[PDB]
Length: 129
Length: 129
Length: 129
Image (tube, rainbow over all chains, first blue to last red; front, top):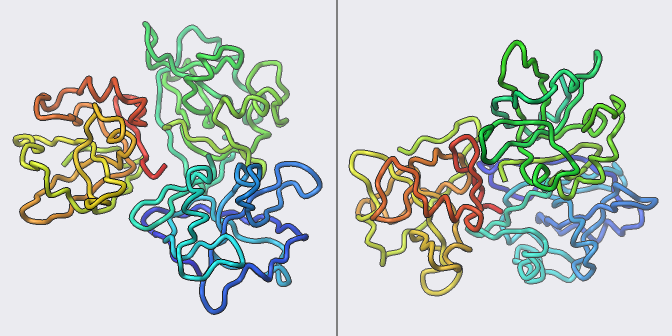
């Protein structure tokens, strides 16, 4: 379970998971691993979420939150997406080739276009704007 | 009473109603009807609210929230304005010629300039920014 | 203690105070006095806060909140910074040459670039965006 600042508050909603995702590659071992997800605005998988592709500007524009409470595509096709929270930067990795418990420079570098603000070692975000 | 997502939270404040508005045309029958209101920034009616005119860019720029808890100009010249909430899109109609309980395409189409974000069938908004 | 709208909520965090500031000039007499602070993004004093300089665009861009609960550099080198609140405009003065309990025209005039919104006599702000 990824830590987050209780004082800041959390807003989360369930979303259907994109079936075409190799969701199993988006765990870490015993340790928590947060990642960003984007929503498909239109098309056949509209309203389904998938791991944000930082190299695709439309994926970046449609980020909807972070997966902070794990996932289990085989047990449930819905995933809890946190749209607003403050999350320590060490827990967010956007890729399989990204060490756990280490801030991801790809995310930190893309924070402006991701609408992330880093304050006191946390990403602050609210994808309801 | 217009439904809204309790989990998201609500922030609301009373505002004086613009006296020059035919407020009676801004009910629906037995059913709830949310609409956007804008504030007059200056002038003699400064700080008074009126139904947003989607065809007037200055009205759009000065939206201050939605009327979600009804109004009664004859019983009280103040109206409770919700500045931040998440409201199902079916309940918001911006005009007399707009069927109740049907999403209003004029609002949906203007959501970007209105600073509305549609997520899971709700308008999310916060006019304190 | 500066008043603020309880209904709106408050989010605050402690920050180290910039040691090079004449912090004693940032009290008012018996009366409360709120002011904006900015964070140093980088450099030797990174993550330390100092009173925003409205005439420096980089200071304006790095505002992080308001000091609403007083300060005491000699008793504690940390100051509680309110990143999100709604504060009556009479209490915020950004300078020694600014009368207490009087809205500061320098702040009001710079509200757009400060990301302050004035609603019903309060500054609304959220520097987590």
